[PDB]
Image (cartoon, coloured by chain):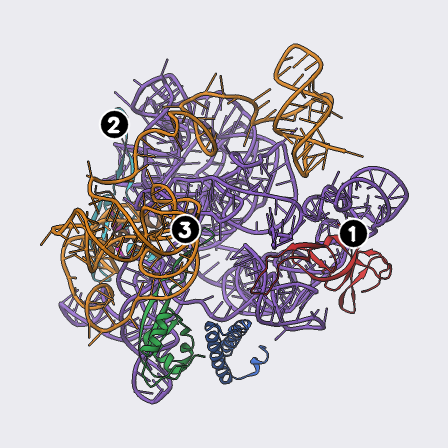
Chain colours: A cyan, B red, C brown, D blue, E green, F orange, G purple
Amino acid sequence: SRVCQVTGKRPVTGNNRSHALNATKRRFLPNLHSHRFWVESEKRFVTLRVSAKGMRVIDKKGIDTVLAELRARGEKY
Amino acid sequence: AAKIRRDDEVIVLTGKDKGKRGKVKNVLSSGKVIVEGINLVKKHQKPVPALNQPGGIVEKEAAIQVSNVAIFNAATGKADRVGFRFEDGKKVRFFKSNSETI
Amino acid sequence: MKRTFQPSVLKRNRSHGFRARMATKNGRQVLARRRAKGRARLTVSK
Amino acid sequence: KAKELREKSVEELNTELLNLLREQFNLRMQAASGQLQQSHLLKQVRRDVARVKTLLNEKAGA
Amino acid sequence: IREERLLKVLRAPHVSEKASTAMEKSNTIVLKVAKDATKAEIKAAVQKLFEVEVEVVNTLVVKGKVKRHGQRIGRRSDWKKAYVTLKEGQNLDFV
RNA sequence: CGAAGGUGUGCUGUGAGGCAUGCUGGAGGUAUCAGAAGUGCGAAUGCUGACAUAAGUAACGAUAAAGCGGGUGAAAAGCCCGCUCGCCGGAAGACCAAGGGUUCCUGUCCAACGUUAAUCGGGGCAGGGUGAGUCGACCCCUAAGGCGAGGCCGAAAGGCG
RNA sequence: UAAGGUGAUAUGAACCGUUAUAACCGGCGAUUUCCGAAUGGGGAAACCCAGUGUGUUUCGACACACUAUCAUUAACUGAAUCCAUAGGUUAAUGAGGCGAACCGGGGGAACUGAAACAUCUAAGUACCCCGAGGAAAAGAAAUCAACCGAGAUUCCCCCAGUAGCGGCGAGCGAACGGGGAGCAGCCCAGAGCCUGAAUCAGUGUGUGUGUUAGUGGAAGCGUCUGGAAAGGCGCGCGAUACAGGGUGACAGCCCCGUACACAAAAAUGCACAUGCUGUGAGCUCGAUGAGUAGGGCGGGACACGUGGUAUCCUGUCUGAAUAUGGGGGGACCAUCCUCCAAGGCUAAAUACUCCUGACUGACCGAUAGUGAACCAGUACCGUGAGGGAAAGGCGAAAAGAAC
């Protein structure tokens, strides 16, 4: 599925309200990307599927922390 | 806790036999009893060659409701009602009027 | 003339047979509804 | 029975069980030839069997 | 094989004109046996229990008929029939 | 010493109605004043059951076809036996697969079933009947196609492989 | 508990028992073929084919046990590639499926209404999907109020069809405040001191209490009518029992019962007691949840349809302050008041009935009442999903009509 492995962002739903306000079902997808990150302590490249948001958060926290929360939540990376 | 039993002498309260006395052959589950010389019916029997049973009208004894028969007190000569007490450690029957055991 | 039901056993059982139902979500819902209505036989089996 | 059987060892019980199956066999043999008068016998043995078996178990069980 | 199983195999002698015919003419007996028993076990069981020599056992399965009792439709149970060939030096016992 | 209900008859009220009572019935009914209503039927091409009508009328399923003697039997155009006649014969014959599931064979019965009778039956009831190393299925091997560990994908279910 | 029994349609045969190993009722046990999550492989469900390891046995084969996946932990193994990881095998622990309604989350209509119809409505309903428990959810203020104050949530009645929202149409619809039901508060983001010290969980034992079989349980005769009395007439008696049912018509006193008074070998529900092991009290000093708050853009939730629209949620792009601080007080600003977000647990009052027991009804009485008073989700109809009937009453007793 499209799910951010970091922030847990998922597809959500909403509408097109047109100019005449005709409401129509739609979705908002997370913005997702398959990316290789450098883990120094493991000396290795982990590949996560993450949103832009996720990436930014990886910059802030460091990747060690993030992966610690991936083993904690118990989801495989 | 069963009041009327095999071989008790009873007197009949109700029916064509009212007042007659007799001896219990057996009891049935439905609360019916079958009493000696009591409630004869005339039954027609199709002759059966396997059992060598002739035909004819057999007088037989038909079950009577156990509510209708009373346990006969031989002491008082009256119909009685029955009750239970514990003598020794054993459950025993007695007559209500003279409160004597059976 | 040629009518609509031309029977076959292998066909019958692959299409509606027990195992065929159990294969899927929907089928097990059928078997649920039947067990709830309390049928004599659920599926077509011999 | 069943007190009587309880005081016998496991071996003698196996032996009794086999006797019983011979007797049972023999019985339903007689019964299927129409040679049986006393039917009540089948039930007698058919149940005794169970008794024996139910002991064997608890002697192994504990 | 175990003997305990054996004594459970053979239900009953099958009685009929066909039966009598084979028993007289071809030296063969006819048995109702447990639905699950096999040619091995029947060979074993006759050879054991009647103590006579079996040549070969042929079998078939009889589908019970369908009956009506008081409008109700029942089904008579299935069962298994066995033609049991005795080696000729044998002569029948019925017990 | 005969309730409700059914059927009559008689009387009485402006009316829906009421009272009494002969038969039937064989154990429940209910004054009075109040209370609550699944409260009143002829229609709805109303819904269920029952019985009419046309009418003892149309019809009895291939225009291949029957006739006689004897048997059985309550009763024989139709059943069994014999004799002639006639129809199919690249089938209206014989053997399978499929599909059915005991309809097979014997005895026995004739209510219903059989478009008539039926003593007959694929009908009823009871019994018997299906014997495999080498015929099939199973089994060994794969086709299209299916399912599909991990895997890829997808809001969830799930899709693809 | 017992003098009768071997379930029913349903007789009989063959028996078992009568003072307690007949039967019957309950407690714990034993057995529990095959299918089915189905789990050794497969499969057209109730079948087909195995492997490994023990154990015999004359050595023909038989018996018995283990063998699913997936998650997690361990152990051993172990490529590309040196370490390493991936991977591979064994082992222990758990999960999978079913089920009525209620519950929280993920998706989510249209008919209809608007006397047409698009916003709106219907309605976050039907339905689908996931997850859970006997309840769940919610929950200890970055809450409201109004210069006086309240003090978590849930639920009921008001406030009020008001304030408002709305093609200002159709409609929708609060809150503040008040009366009640119920009431309970806690921990982590850390050190020191005194340490098993509150609580809570596990387990034994004791008594008490409920449940699962049970025991006793009052007092009536005569007479007419009649097939039969319980009915009429006469004289009695019981009542902490005149609930109700049955017996040849309508019985307090014939039978079962009913009020009342009792009982558990064993298993279980709740209580305190007490022992136990695991869980840590209290105090002092600290500390105080960042890609977060807010913002831009797009939607949604708030009664509130972007409106002057606060307030919450977030797909997207961003982005602070840290008690000399921040949030809210219906645009917004200042003043005044109040509150501390971005960490987590929590009983009760509330909703529901597949199911067990008892009691009741100005509920029905066989075309009614459940589709189903009867062997009914049956026959029968449909390839299938599914549809889906008809059918109660001899009598007191079969005495069911010998000849």
Q: Quadrant of residue G294?
A: top left
Q: Which chain carries label 2?
A: A
Q: How far apart are marks 2 and 3 (CA)?
A: 56 Å
For the magenta stretch, what is the residue range?
Answer: A56-65
Q: Mark 1 points at which residue?
A: B18
Q: B81 or G290: which is nearer to us? A: B81
A60 is within the stretch colored magenta: yes
Q: Distance between the residues labelled 1 and 3?
A: 55 Å
Q: Which quadrant is home to the C terminus of chain A?
A: bottom left
Q: Name the residue under label 2.
A: A18
Name the mark on residue C14.
none
Q: F136 or E30: which is nearer to us? A: E30
- Residue type at tag 1: Lys
- The dominant secondary structure in magenta is helix
Q: Residues within 10 Å of mark 1 (few under 14, many from 20)?
A: few
Mark 1 touches mark 3? (CB < 8 Å): no
